[PDB]
Amino acid sequence: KETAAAKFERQHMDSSTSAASSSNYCNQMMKSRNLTKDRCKPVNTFVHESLADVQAVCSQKNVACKNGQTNCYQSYSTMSITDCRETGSSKYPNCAYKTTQANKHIIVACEGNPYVPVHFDASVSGRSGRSGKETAAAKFERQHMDSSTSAASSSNYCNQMMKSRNLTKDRCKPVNTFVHESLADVQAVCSQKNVACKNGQTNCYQSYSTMSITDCRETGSSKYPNCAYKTTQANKHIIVACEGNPYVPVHFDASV
């Protein structure tokens, strides 16, 4: 029995190729992946990224699913995708498709433990005006949350994450901390130990418990655009600034 996760891989993942280079890509892929077995599936999207990269989207920008559920996630980065759309002349079983390559953000629905993609909801570009505003809370999640892993596993973690979370775009952000706990656990800190922030404001809170965090700090030899970081894994209490309704983290003040 095919699980939802496996079905998503069959229907939507093509890591073998970095992009469609043939107008016959969809014709071939829709067939080989069994998307034309009982009928010509009208439309389908294939993602040309690693499975790791796509699974990672499950811990990226939380957005409402088209069906009204809340378990959808929009990729921080644009990804190589290929849209397949059945041609007007297409007739089962000879299902025919137009192949269109693009680079857009993807939106996937995620479920399970581990938390993995189970549906492809949409693709969105910044040029379309639909990628959306980034709230302070969402920016905090992008810069400071990594719920996908329990801890930094390798010395290249920061090199990878600083780039993928878009913290090396125009320059190398020198220092940044990622938190390896559930979003629920981190949001809960806003009701924990009230303390002054470094800036003298008093909307900061120290987590009661130590948390798994990774400190990323630029090396002495690092130079934009080739930003290099040292990765340090640690268990510390975090201090966040909280704001708004709901009252949620909007800044990472320190770890102690």
Image (cartoon, grey):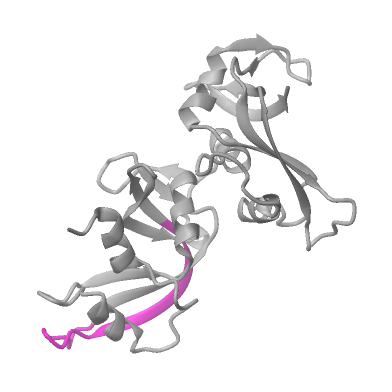
Looking at the image, residue 60 sits to the left or right of residue 68; the answer is: right
- Would you place residue 56 above or below residue 206 in this image? below
Image location of residue 82, percent across then percent down: 39, 74
Looking at the image, residue 18 sits to the left or right of residue 243; the answer is: left
Q: Which residues are magenta?
A: 87-106
Image quadrant in which you'd find residue 54: bottom left
Residue 130 visible (yes or no): no
Task: Determine the residue positioned at 56% across, 38% down.
Answer: 141
Residue 70 visible (yes or no): yes
Q: Quadrant of the N terminus?
A: bottom left
Task: Determine the residue positioned at 25% across, 71% down.
Answer: 43
**Is residue 113 highlighted in magenta?**
no
**Is residue 93 highlighted in magenta?**
yes
Q: Quadrant of the C terminus?
A: top right
Task: Determine the residue positioned at 58% across, 22% down.
Answer: 243
- Would you place residue 204 above or below residue 30 in this image? above
- Would you place residue 132 above or below residue 54 in this image? above
Q: Nearer the viewer, residue 232 or 173?
A: 232
